[PDB]
Each structure stands twice: as C-alpha cells, then as structure tokens.
Image 1 (tube, rainbow over the protein chains, first blue to last red):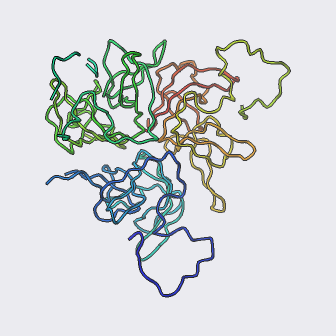
Image 2: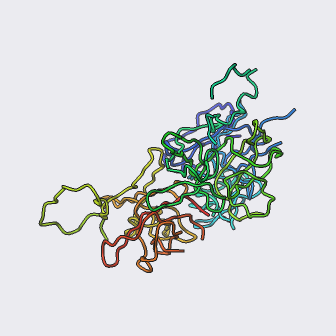
Image 3: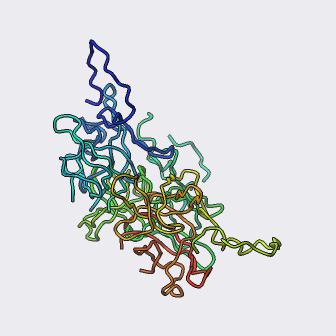
Length: 151
Length: 161
Length: 158
C-alpha cells in the first residue's frame, strides 16, 4: 500500500536530509508545474506508480488498471484508498518522478517501455531512465524517469 | 450548416439525456491549463465545428480546414460565425467530448479514426490510424447529424491496421 | 550568431518610426503567439542550444544532466531562451506545442515555403523533409551569411 498505517512503540531516528526521498510513500513528482493536467479515475487492483490503461465494459463508467503497450493511457502518480480513486497524468503530459521497474537491469541512459503490468522495462519508446533501479523492499524497484510520450 | 440554427410557435418539451444537442458544450470534462487557439476558417468550403482540422497557411492568413488524422493539427471545439473564427484544441492536449461521426451504429469502446472530412469513423476502414481515439458512448442521431462521445489522447506510436 | 543579443555595440540611434517588419531580430526570444497555460522548464546548458531543438545529455554521474542541441530520435524539446549569466536554457517540452522563430539549416533554405513539412537534424536545425510534426509558416529570413531563421509551428510527435 502507498501508506501502510501501522502503530509503532518507538520513534524512528530521522535526521539526515540525504537519501530520504526515494520511498514508496512519496507520491507526486520530483518536479511539478502548475500547468500540469491531472485526472482522477476509478481504479481496480493497485496501479500506484505504474502505467495505466483505460478499461471499458449493470453497466459502469470506464475505470483504469495497470497496463501498457498500445493500450497505455497515462501514469498513476497518487492514490486515495478511501474514495478508491487514482490521480492520473495523461500520456500527453510529460512527467518526472520515480516509477516501478520490472527488475534491477535498468540503468542510466536506458530507454524504457511500459509492459503489460505497467512496469518499466528496457527495450516504441516512452521514457528515458535517469538513475539506476533501487530496491525499496523485496522485489519493488523504483527508477527515476523522464516520461516524454511514445517515441 | 450552423450550430445555433429560429423562431418557434411553441416551446420544445428529466435531467437525463439532455446533453444530446448539436450546440452542446463540446468538453464533457474540461480543465484549466487546456490550451485553446484561434484561427480563421473557410466560410464556404467546409464547416469545421466539432471536426478534426488541419493548418493551411494561405497567402493572406493561416486557415484551418477539415482534415484527416494523418495531417491533423487539432480539434475544432467552437466557432464564432459572426467573425468566422474557429477555436482549436491542439492534438498535444487531451480531449473527452462529443464529435461528429458519419456511422450511426458505433458501440462503446471501439477504436476510431478521423477521415478526410474530419469525421469520426470506425478504425477498421483500412487506413492506418495514427491517433488514439476510443468511443466512450454509442453514436446518437439528432434529427440529421450523428454525434458520439470520444476520448482523444495523443498520437499512436506505430500505425495500426 | 553565438549570442542572442548582438555582441558588439552600435553607433546609431534607432529610428523607431515604423511598425512593420521589426521582429526579425535574433534577440526576439520566446514565441510569437504564446498561451498562458504553457509548461516551461529550464536546464543547464551545454553549448549554445538557443533557438534549436534540444536533447538530453548525460555525464559520468558526478553532475546533473543537461541539454544540448540535437534532434532525430533523441529530441526532447525546443530551447527558446537562455540566461547567459546562469547558463540556464529555457526548454519547452515536445508535448507542449510551440509557435515561434527557429533556426533553419542553411541548405536549400530557398526551397522552404509556407506549408512545407520540417524536421530536426542532429544539430537542432530545422531541415526540409519523420517522427516530429513541424510546419513552416513563412519563408527563410537571413540574419547572417550562415544564420537563417524561419517561423514554424511544432505540434508533437508523428
């Protein structure tokens, strides 16, 4: 989850101001402009920090889920669990931030493609990696990228 | 034709399904930070309202004329007939709204393409599509002009079939 | 040439009596018709990418990335202004359409006419025609024997 709410018994020492931002709970983007277009959409699963595709079908309005390829629609940069809604940056808008990488093979200067699970994998091209993949926890790898569209 | 289109002898007769009007507000979901541009259009060649348009630089001014997806500059969302001015949302911006189609039977979720007349058609016609267009609703006829709710988000990487 | 403003001074006072054909100067930064809703970025400048297409350029890793003149399959945006004191380049992302005066390749510049499709070369210069949608909106204008500028509209990727 984006913010796993767990109670603690001791305070965690947090004084160093470096290597503090690469975390799974840091939503949004590293650099954001006031004129960035944002859309909230109903979602299924957990597409947080992943490429999202718009799925269209009691009939319901279209929702979004993790995906990519020819069906890529945007990027989910923030999520709200109570409302079950996800803030999405459309693919027509450039973005800079940390996204989910398939594995640790991704390095700097690497051109990346959103796979069927919304994860960034090495090689149409969509983004250019800026840093190496870092393991946040278990198999979760986060990579800083500069999304620019589709080739 | 026109958008406003007239004195009536009597008034025309729930909240549901009242948006099915030719002169309805094009943007189903609007957003500030959407870029809107003004251009001139030919007042006798083709009426660009709710159609995909292309830039034609003429010897006196840059006009917008109905065009295909291959050379599309954007979508004409509104027209001021008094000044014959067309308002264009560039293709670089997202769009979700009602556009003119020529097929009266289009289902929801189908892939769509803009033809030479700036008209929504089914993407299975054969021309390789270059834009991501999806039908968000079934096509409806206003009695006659056919309209459909579509979502347009940027160009397609590799042209499809 | 290598500076947005004329490097040398001038020995005359401008007449400032006419209003036609006064925007052909090289120092005319920014776009000709600009929207208030335009996303604008800045980056450290490597070289002089002024009024040229820019691409991302990296280093060993000790320093942050910067932008240099370029194009083709690595195009990232268009540089419209540069602050020389800070060495910062104003960059308009390719996802945001642009309309303004850009540097034109001095090769077949006479053949360029309004309505001619253009594309970016490896040096960030516009050249007559692939993957970037650019349309010339005027004819080439000569500022220096090797410097030609043309009014063009860039509206995304093909």
